[PDB]
Length: 129
Ligand SMILES: Cc1cn([C@H]2C[C@H](OP(=O)(O)O)[C@@H](COP(=O)(O)O)O2)c(=O)[nH]c1=O
Ligand SMILES: [Ca+2]
Image 1 (cartoon, rainbow, N blue to C red):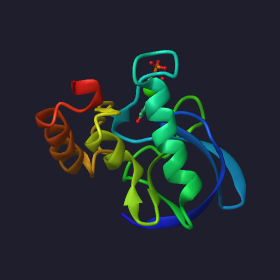
Image 2 (cartoon, rainbow, N blue to C red):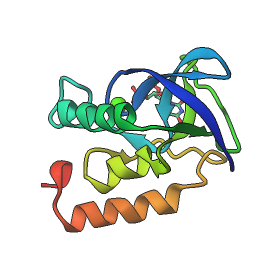
Image 3 (cartoon, rainbow, N blue to C red):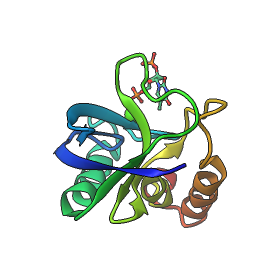
Image 4 (tube, rainbow, N blue to C red):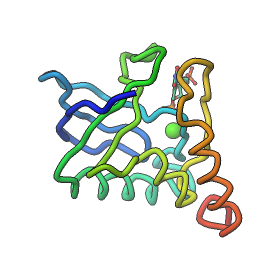
């Protein structure tokens, strides 16, 4: 896989963000994770965590996996990075997202993310508290 440039347009919630990619606005959905909706427990915390990460980044990148690049709602499906740090992993590591939506052929980072989830669960963080 390879990282590609994007720029922040607007934070949306814990696992979606609006980015400009190849010059076009798109809503991205983070691969392999599920944050609570804003109306659910830890939803506002997941939103704030992703907002801070993408707003403070000097450099955002997206990395597509090997499979589907957009979902049925037209959202981009990618791993998002903020100054080299994976958003998807960081949410899981902090107990603000569960590993989820693991479809065959877009699952390159699945075991990296599951290792982060096991760590957050051991630490009883957030969703795992
Ligand atoms: C993360 C992800 C979601 N989706 C679809 C599955 C779910 O469909 P349904 O809307 O029919 O439940 C939805 C979950 O996204 P959200 O968690 O953003 O609601 O997005 C994919 O198709 N591919 C993916 O990789
Ligand atoms: Ca969600």
